[PDB]
Amino acid sequence: RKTQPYDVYDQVEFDVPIGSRGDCYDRYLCRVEEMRQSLRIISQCLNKMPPGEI
Amino acid sequence: ASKVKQDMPPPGGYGPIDYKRNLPRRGLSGYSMFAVGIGTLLFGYWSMMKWNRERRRLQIEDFEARIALMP
Image (cartoon, rainbow over all chains, first blue to last red; front, side, top):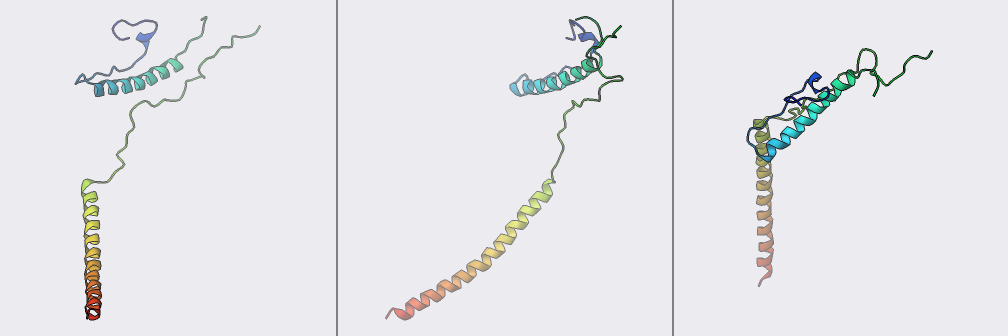
């Protein structure tokens, strides 16, 4: 979504979680933080929905 | 001549949405917990000391009753 964006992913702001140890705990933390960033993106999308055809 | 009606956000915008981690401290200090633990231990030691001394005296009395009855 950051390196090769598609649709309108270049118009939203969010952070990418990055691990340090390459283990299961780091991936669990990454997924939790990804849920938080998804909430962030959802708020931006809700406030920026344009009109027009579908 | 009907105007366009469509599902849109309210004028202005939506209220802010929280997303950051919220994990409060909600605790005491280690010194306080250790102090309470040691205080409880000392109170228990004192109570049990008195109770066990009384129990020793009661056992001595029972043994004296047995000694008086033995012949």
